[PDB]
């Protein structure tokens, strides 16, 4: 009724390539994750009124907890730093040890999927509200997202693009909600050596 994911991310050279490593610890739909699974990501966003869209493609291998995703901004330059979109842009690919596969809400909701909603509050700055559908549509796992960002400072670390293009490791704590809830705090390195925290509040509902 309470476990975590450990997440590690590599961001590689408007465009971003993301390599993700995720495993669970702390304690029917699984058959779609035996192989390598193609992934499609679509995000439509508005931050302080700045509209943008992101499209991503890649594939995931949940038996080892690895994902590779390539993203492009289809509307030109992003109004926010790519690192701030990483957690929004598929926790079904987390590797669960055999002894706790019964807690894998994300795979067991498949193929029908789940709705994933978050509020992400950047400390001393604005917030994102996100709503996503994560599901299989044929042989492909899709993550379809609407993101609304509000209350950001124009000279802050987000709209001012002061975050380093890298990503730290995090623990994502998960408990049963007939869905799940999760809470965690992301740490973003800032170009002046400070850290920008981003509190994540998440609720997932099966479809």
Image (cartoon, rainbow, N blue to C red):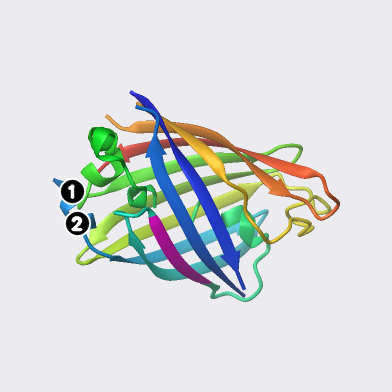
Q: What residue appears at the point 44 percent right and 66 percent down from the top-left corner?
A: 68
Residue 109 can be seen, yes or no = no
Q: Nearer the viewer, residue 126 or 195?
A: 195
Residue 21 can be seen, yes or no = yes
> Is residue 205 positioned above or below 81 on the image?
above
Residue 192: % across, % down: 86, 52
Label 1 sits on a secondary structure element that is helix
Residue of label 2: 32
Q: Which image quadrant is residue 47 in?
A: bottom right
Label 2 sits on a secondary structure element that is helix
Hey, which residue is sitting farthest left in the picture? 28
Range drawn in magenta:
66-71
Residue 4: % across, % down: 43, 34
As measured in the structure, the alpha-carbon distance from the residue carrying label 2 to the one carrying label 1 is 6 Å
Q: What residue appears at the point 68 percent right and 61 percent down from the top-left corner?
A: 165
Residue 164: % across, % down: 73, 58
Mark 1 crowdedness (10 Å alpha carbons): few <14, some 14-19, many ≥20: some
Residue of label 1: 29
Secondary structure that dominates the magenta span: strand
The mark total stands at: 2
User: Image quadrant for the C terminus?
Assistant: top left
Check contact, mark 2 vs mark 1: CB within 8 A.
Answer: yes
User: Image quadrant for the N terminus?
Assistant: top left
Q: Nearer the viewer, residue 105 or 21?
A: 21
């Amino acid at each position: 009724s309470h476990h975590h994911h450990h997440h590690s991310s590599g961001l590689v050279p408007d465009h971003m390539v993301l390599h993700e490593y995720v495993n669970a610890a702390g304690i029917q739909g699984e058959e779609l994750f035996t192989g390598v699974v193609p992934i499609l990501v679509e995000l439509d966003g508005d931050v302080n009124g700045h509209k943008f869209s992101v499209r991503g493609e890649g594939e995931g291998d949940a038996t080892i907890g690895k994902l590779t995703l390539k993203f492009i901004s289809t509307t030109g330059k992003l109004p926010v730093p790519w690192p701030t979109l990483v957690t929004t842009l598929v926790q079904a690919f987390s590797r669960y040890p055999d002894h706790m596969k019964r807690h894998d809400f994300f795979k067991s909701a498949m193929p029908e999927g789940y709705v994933q909603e978050r509020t992400i509050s950047f400390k001393d700055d604005g917030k994102y509200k996100t709503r996503a559908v994560v599901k299989f549509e044929g042989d492909t796992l899709v993550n379809r997202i609407e993101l609304k960002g509000t209350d950001f400072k124009e000279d802050g670390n987000i709209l001012g693009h002061k975050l380093e293009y890298n990503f730290n490791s995090h623990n994502v704590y998960i408990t049963a909600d007939n869905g799940i809830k999760a809470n965690f705090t992301v740490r973003h390195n800032v170009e002046d050596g400070s850290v920008q925290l981003a509190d994540h509040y998440q609720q997932n509902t099966p479809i």
